[PDB]
Image (spheres, coloured by chain):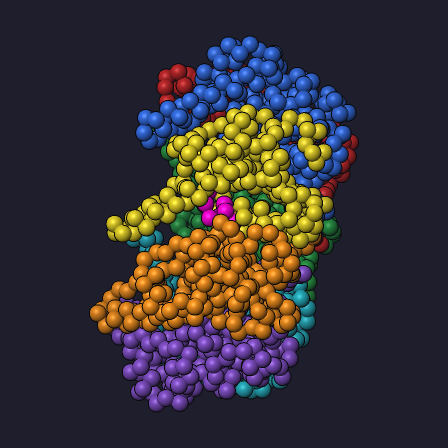
Chain colours: A cyan, B green, C red, D purple, E blue, F orange, G yellow
Amino acid sequence: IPTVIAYDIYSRLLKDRIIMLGSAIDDNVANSIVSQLLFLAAEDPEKEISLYINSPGGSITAGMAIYDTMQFIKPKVSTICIGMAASMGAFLLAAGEKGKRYALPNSEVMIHQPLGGAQGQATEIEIAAKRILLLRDKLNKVLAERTGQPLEVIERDTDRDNFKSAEEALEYGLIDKILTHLEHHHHH
Amino acid sequence: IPTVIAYDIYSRLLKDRIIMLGSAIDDNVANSIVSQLLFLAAEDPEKEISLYINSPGGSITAGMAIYDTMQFIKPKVSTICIGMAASMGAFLLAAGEKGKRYALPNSEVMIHQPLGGAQGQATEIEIAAKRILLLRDKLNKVLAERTGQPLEVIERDTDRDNFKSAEEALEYGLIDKILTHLEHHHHH
Amino acid sequence: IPTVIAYDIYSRLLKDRIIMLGSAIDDNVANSIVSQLLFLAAEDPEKEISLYINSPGGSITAGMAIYDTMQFIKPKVSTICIGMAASMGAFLLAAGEKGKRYALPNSEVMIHQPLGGAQGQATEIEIAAKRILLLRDKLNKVLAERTGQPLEVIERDTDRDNFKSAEEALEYGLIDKILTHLEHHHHH
Amino acid sequence: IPTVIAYDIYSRLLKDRIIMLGSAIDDNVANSIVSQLLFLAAEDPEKEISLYINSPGGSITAGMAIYDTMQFIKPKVSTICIGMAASMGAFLLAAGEKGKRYALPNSEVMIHQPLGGAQGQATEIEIAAKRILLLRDKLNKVLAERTGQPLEVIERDTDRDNFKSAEEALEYGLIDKILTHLEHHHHH
Amino acid sequence: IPTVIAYDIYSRLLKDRIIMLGSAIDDNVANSIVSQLLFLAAEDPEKEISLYINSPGGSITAGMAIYDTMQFIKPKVSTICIGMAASMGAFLLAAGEKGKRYALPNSEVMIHQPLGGAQGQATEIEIAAKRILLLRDKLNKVLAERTGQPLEVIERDTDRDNFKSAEEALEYGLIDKILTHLEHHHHH
Amino acid sequence: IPTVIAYDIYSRLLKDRIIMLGSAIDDNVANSIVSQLLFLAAEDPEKEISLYINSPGGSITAGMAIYDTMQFIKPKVSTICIGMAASMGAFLLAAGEKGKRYALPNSEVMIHQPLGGAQGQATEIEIAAKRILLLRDKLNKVLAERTGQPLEVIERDTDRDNFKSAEEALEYGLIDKILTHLEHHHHH
Amino acid sequence: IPTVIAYDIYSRLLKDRIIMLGSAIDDNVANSIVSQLLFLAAEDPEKEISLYINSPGGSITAGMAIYDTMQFIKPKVSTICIGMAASMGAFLLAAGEKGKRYALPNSEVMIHQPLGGAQGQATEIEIAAKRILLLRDKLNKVLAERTGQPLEVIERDTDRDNFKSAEEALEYGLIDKILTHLEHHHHH
């Protein structure tokens, strides 16, 4: 991370209301991104925010932490898929303000059902199964709302890894526009 | 964690009386959390403090350190569940000023009984067993007073991992309100 | 640990004559605490000092370095138990200035006999045994005086891990008062 | 990396709109380079940018994130191959603004087909197989266009590791010119 | 280690001519202690210096570098045993300026003969044997001179680990006084 | 690395247009060296640069990146061998400005053929074989040009490790002068 | 390493033309030592420099880099042995300016023949043997000139680890004077 004069590159971008997510989503990442979101919203609750997304996914709770925040602050959060928006990453992509969900020409998106683990007594394994099946329904329901796709379709399309091109993601309703030029973005 | 000119993202939020508990609770974390609280209470014993919670919990003793400090200082501590508030995290979530305990739409909460270990001679195992059971009952008593539930209900509901949605947590008495809009908070 | 404005949360508290012990006690930790105590004593040998204790204890020699420095300097050292004060931690807690040894409602204190080990020749094993038995007697005598309990009692009550609640510690004479309010301390 | 009183050598060069890519390409490297590009573009959308490349390659999604950002910003991104530009490194080199894709005299370039893996059920291995074969076409089509070589020539030529000298890279269409002098660069 | 506002806690004490030695003794620690002694000497060759000691000792050559430097520089070096001063650590404690060698009430001191190793041919083991026997004898001669005890007695007393309280240390001649109050120190 | 007030020792020397290369040559080292050369050339493309070389060698491509950059920039680059210049290190040494390639009295240089490895199918092993045999031939031609030795001599002399004294390095044509005094350098 | 005020203890000493070598000699160390030497010589080629030495030795080539640089620069480099100077460390001690090679009362010096390895074909074992033997001879020739002993005696006396007291080192011609007081130093 190079320094700008003193800011680290990411911090310099943060200054222009730009948040970069380019790693898997774990508690730390959500924690950092949530603080950044709250900070900006405090700075100016009216000014829009840009969240770049390039991650393989991660913890469902970490993602919902980021998700609920994006929706909770007044600022509208624009999402840009760069590289790959997989699993919870793709979910955050579609979580962006309607009409402000972008991706780049060669961007990729991948949706699929939650993954988990259960170990121990039958009673414990059942508790885990029940919980992960519930999380899948919640996620699916929210995804159907974001994309405009029927719940039944999300369910069926997420059974196994579903990789999509930037065009397909548009077609599916995961993003609103594919950015090509430095002017295609509404920012300028 | 990015910087803020020269601060640290969390130090930045700290400046606005916001502490972020976003990791497993251990002696380290407890000491940082307690210090931040003591600091803020010194800065202004009148203004309230907001403690965001997103952790899988941890040490009972570390937790109570945070718990006692919360009730100790003059400032009223408001809790906010983001992502997941499990085990001691949930205990702490419910420890915020009555009426100022929050969670976001998709936040999750989980309560369960203490976990521990014992090794050695029968005598030592019994000393340890007596300690954990006693801690369990102590925690149950505080959780009951906090939620309003009857002790016997808390005892049975924590036998196994008990996962709750923000609405279930609200209806249980773990939190007071589910934030949805930036102005749904009592602050803004 | 976050920063304050430049500072460190602990560094910031140190400015208010507050030292935080929240880990196992080893040489490193002891040197830090001691240097902090000497530094504060150099600043104003007349001003009081608050030492927060949340520690499972550790090295006996390391703890005595802290102990001796506490008594050595002019400032009166007040101890406050947070979470857990076990073995040497409990000794340090009881070591605070008579009348200024506090604990919080849910704090725990654990007293027990010294732990150690020895390997090698019978002669070597006897040297260690002789020593650990002597340290225990030295420690027991100090504790008895600091608590008011008769030596015989300290001896029998430490044969095995003895966990005590804030109330029991008060009763045992390990602490002077249990805190709950912000202005009920010696500072107000 | 040495300092420049107070900058980081790489940070100092970033000031002159120079970005050094000198390691394998992963999500970290891509997030840093993409951020540097955005920053520069934000600094002055009119000025050019130099991207020095010397890397063994890396993640395809990480590289495309860099690729898409290069075309996406208004500024022209000139690429200079130094040492070795392999795998996604060569891809990126060829992605520079046409006419401004350079290589020093003894530079090396290596192109080859993607690499990956798959474990699991036939259905899952099929999905992974289809994806990788698809990414291969996608990249091959971009390289075909950037270089002017027909798709199937790119396919056959990248079947096994293909090492090209600077003269061969020029001939192939990967670079526009082999630099020798400092001022010989279109820039100065 | 906390900071003091731009200094390190130890650097702050260094400003008051106080050097802390609270870790095993190796080349590193020695290089730092010597450097500090030299610095303090250049600053004011007339002002006294205090060396707090709490270490299990360590390398002999390292310890002697510190020993010789203490004698070499003009400032009188006062030593204060805190916690434990064993092996080379005890040796350095006894090396303080006569009449200014201290220990706190519950400090501990341990003396013993050198430890070492040897691998290889007979000739090689003999060389090492002679060296360590020589080192032991050298150290014993200094301890004798410093304590006032006869050489024969130092030899017999260090055959095996020999632990002593502060009183026993005083009565043996390893220290000159046991400090109790912040006023018992020759300083104030 | 110590500091000079506030640069780090290498930064301080970088200010006098002196670059230090005292480690094995890998992409990371190459990237730092190249960036230093570029920075200096940007600072003042007229003044000469001094490159101190003490390294066992390393990556051929990492070395060539440095090689090319040296020739690439406007500033003439003087090389000085201290300790040892082996393999690619010796190569860089010889790559210094003609007449300005130095070595100290007891400096050591070594030349040998490239090292590498191959694993996998015969086809893949052939690709690796042809490439290392090509690189060797490429390096050999540059060494011949830089030393004045006929290719055939360079080929036979690099078959096995070939260590040379500073004087032998001079007679071979690897360097031009053997420094002894502070003025024997063309700078003074 | 503590800080002196904006300065690292060693850095503070470097200001007074004092370089501390208290570790094994590897490429890193040599690089840092050579740089500090060049720096000091650039700062003022007239003022002498003091190189303290407490090191087990290490790489021969790294050692010679330091050696050649000490002789090379104009400033006279005084060496002071503290603790132990072995292998290349003793070589460097003996390398100081004639008449300015010191040692402290209990300092120790050790000389031995080079150590190395060799694996592979008989031809390569031979290349390695000749070199190790060549290096031994080169080093013994330099040590002889600087000590006054004939090569023949230097070789014999280093066949095996040869530990010498400060007094023995003086008589052998490795040092010129054994310092005792801070006045017996020509600088003071």
Q: Which of the 4 image quadrants contains residue F122?
A: bottom left
- Give me the residue at 70% from left, 47% from top: G46
User: Where, quadrant-wise, is the C terminus of chain F in this rendering?
Assistant: bottom right
A142 sits left or right of E7 in the view: left
- Give me the residue at 40% from left, 67% from top: F149
Horizontal and vertical percent position of residue E56: 52, 28
The magenta stretch is G56-65
A77 sits left or right of B186 in the view: left
A131 sits left or right of B176 in the view: left
Q: Nearer the viewer, residue E49 or G135?
A: G135
- Give me the residue at 53% from left, 11% from top: E151
Answer whether residue F179 is magenta in the image.
no
Residue F76, compared with residue A127, is above or below; it is below
- Give me the residue at 46% from left, 48% from top: G61
Q: Nearer the viewer, residue G64 or E117?
A: G64
Horizontal and vertical percent position of residue F164: 41, 54
Question: As drawn, which residue projects farthest toward the left?
Answer: F122
Q: Nearer the viewer, residue G78 or D137?
A: G78
Q: Nearer the viewer, residue D37 or G59?
A: G59
Decide whether the magenta segment is chiefly helix, strand or loop. Answer: helix
Is residue C64 in view?
A: no
Residue B74, compared with residue G148, is above or below; it is below
Horizontal and vertical percent position of residue B57: 49, 50
Is residue C44 in view?
A: yes
Horizontal and vertical percent position of residue A87: 41, 70
B136 sits left or right of F3 in the view: left
Q: Which of the 4 image quadrants contains residue E173?
A: top right
Total tally of numbered discs in the picture: 0
